[PDB]
Image: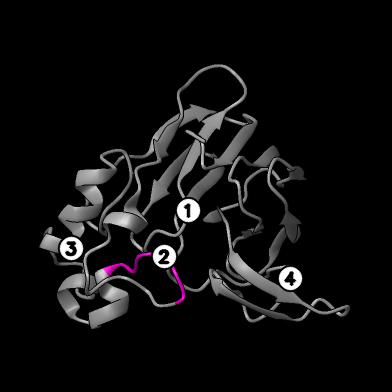
Amino acid sequence: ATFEIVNRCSYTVWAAASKGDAALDAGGRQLNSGESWTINVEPGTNGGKIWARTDCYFDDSGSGICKTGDCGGLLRCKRFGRPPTTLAEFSLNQYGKDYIDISNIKGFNVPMNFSPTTRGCRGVRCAADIVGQCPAKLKAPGGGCNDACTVFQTSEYCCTTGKCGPTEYSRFFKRLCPDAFSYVLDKPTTVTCPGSSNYRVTFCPTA
């Protein structure tokens, strides 16, 4: 119900929180190095995601653009962010439980730790330097490292028929970040927590 979004990176980022068809709390906010943003997420939200955006520019009305994770050019996101985007995923109060995970299925742009601040479970993280190690063909000019489905648009990478296996590209993300989904059908890396737990999403955790 309460998430703290901390930016431990030495660079500014524009946090974002959405569930695809609506914002979570204010949906987005500028987050300078060291600043923390506290938001409230309604119990039961399904398919919620938190992520960071880099190199953004917003006018007074709140309209603009970012190089990674841009959401329809809005400061306060309603829709999901545009790849590459390391994703903090969660579905709350699902059958008495809470479910969280980190995903690289949509690429990686910023290192991240996702941990409960209440008891009953553990957190997950993906802090390796994926952007610096990013394969030549996946590097995104705007910054970040694209997932292979975003770059090649193939049934295999996008797991279109719900029938797909790991790939050299998915193995890259998996190699650097074991505890994060590297592709749609990756062995679940989801964590189960008590219903209504509180959480903290830290960007650049080992920074």
Q: Name the spot of residue 153 as percent of width and height, x first.
A: 25, 83
Bounds of the magenta segment = 142-147
Residue 192, quarter of the rendered image: top left
Q: Nearer the viewer, residue 199 or 13?
A: 13
CA–CA distance between discs 1 and 2?
A: 7 Å
Nearer the observer, disc 1 or disc 4? 1
Q: Which is more N-terminal, label 2 or label 3?
A: 2
**Horizontal side, residue 178 vs residue 107: left or right:** left
CA–CA distance between discs 4 and 2?
A: 19 Å
CA–CA distance between discs 3 and 2?
A: 15 Å
**Disc 1 marks which residue?**
110
Q: Residue at x 30, y 67 (%)?
A: 147
**Disc 4 marks which residue?**
75
- Which amino acid is tagged 4? Leu
Q: Name the spot of residue 20 as percent of width and height, x first.
A: 58, 68
- Position of residue 135 relative to residue 152, above or below, is above
Q: Residue at x 13, y 65 (%)?
A: 164
* Disc 3 and disc 4 in contact, CB within 8 angstroms: no
**Disc 2 marks which residue?**
144
Category of crowding for the residue at label 2, using alpha-carbon neighbours closer than 10 angstroms: few (below 14), some (14–19), many (at least 20): many
Q: Which is more N-terminal, label 3 or label 1?
A: 1
**Disc 3 marks which residue?**
169
Category of crowding for the residue at label 1, using alpha-carbon neighbours closer than 10 angstroms: few (below 14), some (14–19), many (at least 20): many
* Disc 1 and disc 3 in contact, CB within 8 angstroms: no
- Position of residue 206 relative to residue 91, above or below, is above
- Which amino acid is tagged 1? Val
Q: Residue at x 40, y 41 (%)?
A: 127
Q: Which is more N-terminal, label 4 or label 3?
A: 4
